[PDB]
Image (spheres, rainbow, N blue to C red):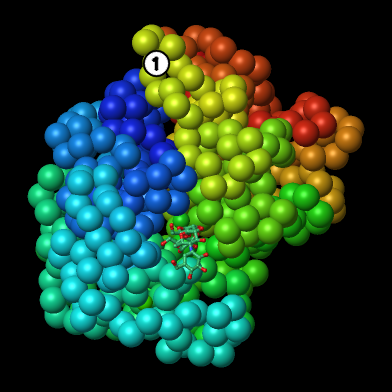
Amino acid sequence: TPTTFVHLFEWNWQDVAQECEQYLGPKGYAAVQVSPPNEHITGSQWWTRYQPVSYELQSRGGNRAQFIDMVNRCSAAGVDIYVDTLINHMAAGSGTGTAGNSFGNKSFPIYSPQDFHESCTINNSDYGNDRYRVQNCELVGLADLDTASNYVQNTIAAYINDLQAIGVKGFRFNASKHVAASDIQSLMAKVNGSPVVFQEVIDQGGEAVGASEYLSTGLVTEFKYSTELGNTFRNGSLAWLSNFGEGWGFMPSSSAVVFVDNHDNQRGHGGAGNVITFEDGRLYDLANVFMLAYPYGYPKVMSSYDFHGDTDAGGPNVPVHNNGNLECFASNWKCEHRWSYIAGGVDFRNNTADNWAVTNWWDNTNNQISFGRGSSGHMAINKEDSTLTATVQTDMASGQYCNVLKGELSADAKSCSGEVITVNSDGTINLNIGAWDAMAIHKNAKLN
Ligand SMILES: C[C@H]1O[C@H](O[C@H]2[C@H](O)[C@@H](O)[C@@H](O[C@H]3[C@H](O)[C@@H](O)[C@H](O)O[C@@H]3CO)O[C@@H]2CO)[C@H](O)[C@@H](O)[C@@H]1N[C@H]1C=C(CO)[C@@H](O)[C@H](O)[C@H]1O
Ligand SMILES: [Ca+2]
Ligand SMILES: [Cl-]
């Protein structure tokens, strides 16, 4: 069962199409979030994608034909496409777009100055006490669309419906806290069918606008998850995670989209240094293992590029699939979705989807934890400086299983490529996990 999606940040359409066929489909990823495919301002910075000029599908990722090719190929491989949709604003200032269209003074190919709110600036203090300014003023000078206007709603809905017609299955509504939830309710009434929609709402608490206001229009990004997980893995105790989720004050599990990090917070935009990213190596593997094994929310794995400290920089000048070479793991594309522990965690989640409970939780009161998903699977993380050798109880059938974080079961089910884990006749496992390592086993990776 598909349970996890991935964000292939700044990947062009040809690269995404091949990745769906060679990796994502076979490994079981449910979908892919792509960078904004609509016309945007020229420039090499990654953020140019968030300044639209029109809704024509001509962007840094490729042209319309290439985009369509990608949706078809991915769809054939069993992988959905989620489009990052800009519903709050248009580009700032004046210039030219990726399809040749020029714009200026709040005048675009599809919008006139009267289709925007009167200009004003959102100040940092407005988030805590002025809901009106947060939703009607400009975010960093971006022209603010009059989202209450029937013309504007019809225009955005037509783009969304056009994308569904092509075959797109879902949408990420970017900068949603800056649009009144009621404006989104009206917009959705114009959208055909019921696609998967997740709204980017950054709410850490104490804001004039809350994430709970968006629960009725689709899923919502739970940013507290990313910050609390990072804070616990770096400065707290893993034993504290025994009741992670609604117990910590997060939104309902069935409404939340979660992640260890995202494209914004891994570079400072809306997230502090406690956020864990690819730069943290093994800490990142372990954080992902917990997230994928834990039954809270709909997770999305991050897929980045080494930005070399430059937070405005765009991606590598070389494709991922470069003439038979995979430009992964080095100083170009990081390809975290291909990392053994992460891919292994996705497999665990997919195979324990018939039991969403946390059973037999165990911890050493600090950084050693273990828990199961009933008879469907069991896992353990060791973040202490010495070997975890405790005997833990599971609800699994006795036998030998592959630690899917380090390998996989052969086609004939007679061998594993990584270490074997034994479940004794009484259901117990005598653990043997080194410092900063983990293990996960499930009922569909049992040796014959
Ligand atoms: C016009 C504006 O362009 C750039 O701003 C970027 C952000 O740096 C980038 O993070 C991204 O913003 C997203 C944000 O991270 C996310 O939380 C939110 O939900 O969605 C945002 C995208 O919609 O994209 C924007 C837009 O490209 C520059 O970094 C900014 O400096 C720049 N502001 C300029 C321009 C003007 C007016 O001409 C001044 O008012 C402004 O002070 C100046 O700095
Ligand atoms: Ca707005
Ligand atoms: Cl997000």
Please tell me which residue is depicted at 79% across the width and 43% down the height of the picture.
Answer: 368
At a point 57% along the width and 19% down the height, the residue shown is 407
User: Is 6 left or right of 111, judged from the image as shown?
Assistant: right
Identify the residue at image location x=82%, y=31%: 435
Q: Residue sitting at 53 percent across and 10 percent down?
A: 415
> For this view, does 447 lie left or right of residue 70?
right
Judge the density around disc 1: few (<14), some (14-19), many (≥20) Cα neighbours within 10 Å: few
Image quadrant in which the N terminus is located = top left
Residue 38: % across, % down: 25, 50
User: To which residue does mark 1 refer?
Assistant: 322
Nearer the observer, 200 or 75: 200
Q: Is residue 391 visible?
A: no
In this view, 120 is above or below 339? below
Residue 241 occupies quadrant: bottom right
State whether residue 224 is above or below residue 226. Answer: below
Measured from the top left, where is residue 163 in percent x and y?
17, 51
**Most extreme residue toward the right, as rendered?**
386
